[PDB]
RNA sequence: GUCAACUGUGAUUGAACAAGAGUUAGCCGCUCCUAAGGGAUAGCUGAAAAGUGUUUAAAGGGGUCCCCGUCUCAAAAGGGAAACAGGUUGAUAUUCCUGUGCCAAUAGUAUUAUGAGUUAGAUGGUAACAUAUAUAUAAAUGAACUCCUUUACAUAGGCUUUACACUCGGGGUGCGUUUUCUUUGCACUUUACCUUUAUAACAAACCUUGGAAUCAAUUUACUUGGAGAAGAGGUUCGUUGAACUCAAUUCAAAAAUUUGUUUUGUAGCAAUAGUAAUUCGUAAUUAUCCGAAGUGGUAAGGACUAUCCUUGAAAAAAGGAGGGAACGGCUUUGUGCUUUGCUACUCUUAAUACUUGUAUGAGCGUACCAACAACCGCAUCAGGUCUCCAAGGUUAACAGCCUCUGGUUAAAUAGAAAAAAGUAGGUAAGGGAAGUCGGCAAAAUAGAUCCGUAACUUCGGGAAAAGGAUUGGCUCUGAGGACAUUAUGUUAACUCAGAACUGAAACGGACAAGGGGAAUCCGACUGUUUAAUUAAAACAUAGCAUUGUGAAAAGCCACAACUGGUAUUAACA
């Protein structure tokens, strides 16, 4: 839990990084967003 | 000590006197807890059911 | 002591458990917890410390013995038989 | 930390090159009293001087190169 | 706890090497700490030999 | 007063995790885990603790000064002086007996 | 920032949404070790898949050709090398910061300093045993090969020691009540690791002397003694952790090293840091910080005692002992070895320089929640979900009840009305189970002290049997300690027992808290069981009894095969 190892740490930061919405600068030339309580990672 | 008689080679060894702790089974067993402790260090042979 | 009329030390088990068995237990338990005489050192400090094992407190020596008292007759008879020849 | 009861030992420690600084502080008048704490890299040695004037004279006479530290 | 019989720690001396070696023997009634125990063809008849 | 909080990680009261609360210079009640109780050095043949020799955990026993670890006389911290005496007497008698038997036998 | 959706009512709120920021370790864990265990090697079986695990081994380590000797993973609560205090940020901190320290290291050669030893290896003490205080308690000859020990252990019961906690009383600071009464109520009066911590103290252990029965010493407890007690004089371990002359100084005496008087010190760390303050500037200063003692709530230790047909892990890692291999420096023939000649030298820690890849500190974790919405239950679900910290009054009490510190005043809604009906509750004249399958429900009873207690019984119980009495408040009386003057004082905790008076006769005044008796039937008993319609007369159990079996060609059972298990066994099995 509090305790973790490097692969879990990296993946959680990856999932956090991924979650952020689509950028609007691309859009002017869809989304899958996760909400933590409703959808668990299932790792 | 079963009463059995047997003929064995002369060179076979043995240890003089009787085994220690004689009379062990002749104290009355008081209770189920005593039986639990005896079997606790033996094996899953008790209770039989 | 004078607390019990005749039950004595098996008064710890009390009214629970059949009486004849309590009498049988009384004889074994009395033998078990007695302080026996040590052959080596001449004091009455020999007690049972584990099932077949009797240690004297004073001289700190472990004699292997019977279950409920130090000696059976069997070993004595054998011992005398070996000695005589 | 270790307290020192001998001026000669105090000077002998002081003269070692592991000494870096000496720290002085004077305490409440009941009559005043002076704690001189000497700083070697290994340890902080303390000597309690009853007389400030004696302590200050000893401190000035000891190794005038080394740093002096004052708590007020 | 598994055995019904006391064990006896007997010290023997190595014969092909230097120093003391300990064995674990089954106790006999009347055996005692500091007893000398003998084993072999040329052993005398005595309890625990 | 205030309650304490653990500081030492692994926050349980096991046999190796026994604790003394202490109030600080900050006036705060805090906790220290004491070093474990250690068995004493003994006479091997008597199985009993011996004089002079300090009782220390093996870490402290490794740092400990050499005078503390043992006794100067004969078989040092391994066995006690009364044990040593008995062995010396026995050793002396057995040699005396051995020579007398050799003289005696023919 | 923020309000589209969500936030079962509202909503500007938000654990929602958008943007950013945030987790820093030689010392805290993992990381290392083995356990219960898992996977393989050696083999051998099996078509293979797989099944096994020393079981027909020419395989891993240490020494100077010998000696050991299957491997590996498996504990974030077992074992285990080392850090604390104060401060600090919007959010981290044993980790940042400041101070103090501690730990594992730390290669080669050359310098230097530190003590030893020499003309090759110290001493003291009758003894138990002790001794290197160098900045730094550093080294007190020692090889092979050995032998030990720490690591390292159940449960229960009391006694005892300390700490933290709690309390009472005094002085000092500030704040509060203050008509009346209060020489008052409250807050604050702080002190860590570390320094073989130094000493003192004490339960034990051990030793010299001593020589005990008219037994003594002696604990709550019983223990101990001619295998040497009491006594007398020591010594050690362990607790502890600045106690106590402890250290310094003074003057007097031994003396030109000990004791008495004076002066210092929160032992150093340490006040400068903390805390209650106090002024001034608009960051700075000043003033403060300690005397007596009791309660026994927690925890740890100690010496023990008692019990088990139960005697309650291991290794890594470390230390101690035995043993007696080896042995000066400079020079050289002869043959690394030997004879000649010489003698400030040989050891040993620490610091320094020079060389040798770059000669100090690996890597991962560290946010927040831990459910009162973050975890699981399809969900901000009254369910479930592991551990520790534990204040005052009342009391047997950590129960129940109220209170201080800390926390909160939100629970998927609010308001207004107040009948039925529902539901959780109360209360009822006279009767008292006559209602109903059923006294179901509800109530009665219940705490202490003092009395009193039967049938019956395996004599242990029955038993709190039954059956009674008492209990508040107030003012007293009596009993139980510690110190020091030779009979007199100084002085502390609280618990017991008795007597009055007193009152709407009321007092275990709330509060917790048993209904009882006469019998039958069944099961002896403590135990166990139908998770979510089943706790019993069922199962287990002690006791009684039977059978088979003497061992690798045995019993009984498991495996496809080889092979296992019972078996770390052995007919008291």
Image (cartoon, rainbow, N blue to C red):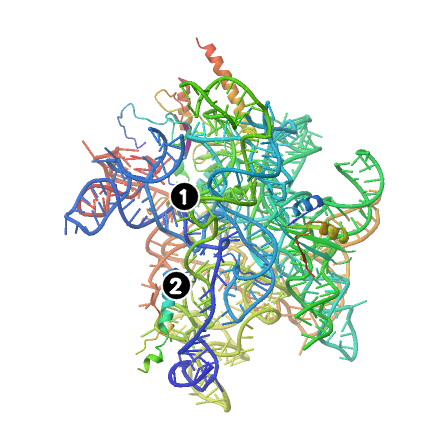
- Pointer 2 local density, CA inside 10 Å: few below 14, some 14–19, many at least 20: few
Q: Does the magenta segment cover residue E2? A: no
The answer for how far apart the CA atoms under marks 1 and 2 are is 60 Å
Residue E31 showing in the rendered view: yes
Along the line of sight, which residue is nearer the eye, C40 or G85?
G85
Task: Tell me the number on the disc at residue A9.
Answer: 2
Residue G162, placed above or below residue B22: below
Q: Is residue B45 left or right of residue F13?
A: left
Task: Tell me the number on the disc at residue C75.
Answer: none
Q: Is residue G155 left or right of residue G118?
A: left
Prevailing SS of the magenta stretch: strand
Q: Chain of mark 2?
A: A
Task: Tell me the number on the disc at residue B29.
Answer: 1
The residue located at (57%, 29%) in the rendering is F73
**Which of the image's four quarters has the N terminus of chain F?**
bottom right
Q: Is residue G4 left or right of residue F48?
A: left
Residue G540, placed above or below residue G566: below
Q: Which residues are magenta?
A: E8-13
């Amino acid at each position: 839990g509090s305790i973790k190892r490097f692969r879990l740490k990296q993946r959680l930061g990856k999932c956090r990084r991924q979650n952020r919405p689509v950028p609007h600068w691309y859009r002017l030339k869809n989304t899958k967003r996760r909400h933590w309580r409703r959808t668990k990672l299932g790792l | 000590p079963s009463g059995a008689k047997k003929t064995i080679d002369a060179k076979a060894r043995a240890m003089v006197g009787v085994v220690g702790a004689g009379g062990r089974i002749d104290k009355p067993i008081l209770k189920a807890g005593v039986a639990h402790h005896k079997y606790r260090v033996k094996r899953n042979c008790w209770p039989k059911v | 002591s004078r607390r019990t009329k005749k039950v004595g030390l098996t008064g710890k088990y009390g009214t629970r458990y059949g009486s004849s068995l309590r009498k049988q237990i009384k004889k074994i338990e009395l033998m078990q917890h007695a302080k026996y005489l040590c052959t080596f050192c001449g004091k009455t400090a020999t007690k049972r410390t584990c099932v077949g094992i009797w240690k004297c407190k004073k001289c700190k020596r472990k004699v292997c013995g019977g279950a409920w008292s130090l000696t059976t007759p069997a070993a004595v008879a054998a011992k005398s038989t070996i000695i005589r020849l | 930390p270790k307290q020192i009861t001998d001026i000669r030992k105090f000077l002998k420690i002081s003269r070692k090159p592991d000494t870096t600084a000496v720290i002085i502080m004077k305490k409440k008048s009941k009559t005043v009293i002076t704690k001189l704490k000497l700083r070697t890299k290994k340890y902080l040695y303390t000597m309690v001087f009853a007389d400030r004037k004696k302590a200050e004279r000893i401190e000035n006479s000891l190794l005038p190169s080394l740093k002096r530290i004052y708590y007020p | 706890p598994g055995r019904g019989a006391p064990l006896a720690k007997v010290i023997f001396k190595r014969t092909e090497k230097y120093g003391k070696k300990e064995e674990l023997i089954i106790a006999s009634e009347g055996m005692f700490t500091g007893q000398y125990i003998s084993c072999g063809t040329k052993a005398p008849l005595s309890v625990g030999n | 007063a205030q309650r304490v909080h653990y500081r030492r990680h692994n926050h349980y009261n096991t046999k190796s995790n026994k604790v003394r609360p202490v109030r600080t210079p900050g006036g705060k009640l805090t906790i220290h885990v004491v070093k474990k109780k250690a068995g004493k050095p003994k006479c091997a043949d008597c199985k009993t603790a011996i004089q002079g020799v300090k009782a220390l955990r093996p870490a402290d026993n490794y740092r400990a000064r050499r005078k503390n670890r043992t006794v100067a006389r004969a078989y040092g911290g391994s066995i006690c002086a009364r044990c040593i005496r008995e062995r010396i007497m026995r050793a002396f008698l057995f040699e005396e007996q051995k020579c007398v038997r050799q003289v005696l036998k023919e």
